[PDB]
Image (cartoon, rainbow, N blue to C red; front, side):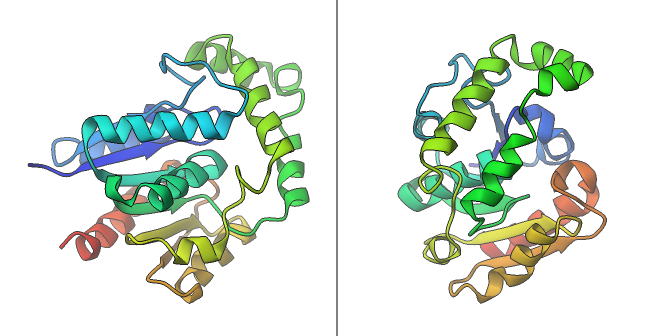
Length: 230
């Protein structure tokens, strides 16, 4: 009788982790299902070598189990998987929010972003120690499975075409921060992609919009939902 919202994190985050302020504001009003992707958080499944394919199949099972709902996908894990869920299973998704994400990234721009994670455990011991707590020791294996999959097949994993967002058959919001120029332009340019794609830029926010500027993150989504789901 109530709608449901699914929250899908980015690389090495968690459902509850990336979306803590969102779950607090919306639970009681909505059924909130923070999803832990394979190899992350409390998820019972470890990462698979064809990570994105397996993770999308896991995400599809989640929505098919708890019923159709609203998808929020963050970063270059949740984003692409949420979009592919909305593109291949419109029967499961009532609307889609893409956040901290930019279509049509060049493969070399992206792999260079992934390089930032190379040697993370050796260079950021404090971050490495929280990962062991959040994820288990398997996060090292999880990071390798994800980076490997994008290395072999950037186009069918981390890449989302703006044209493919326009072809979505459900209401879509691109909700990015202003700090990363590539994300800001995407949120600015989304209405011109040729569907009903909506864009909104959240001031003072960077890559993790929902965590940086929670108050205005929730308002932009709520505003979007009132138009989409009325």
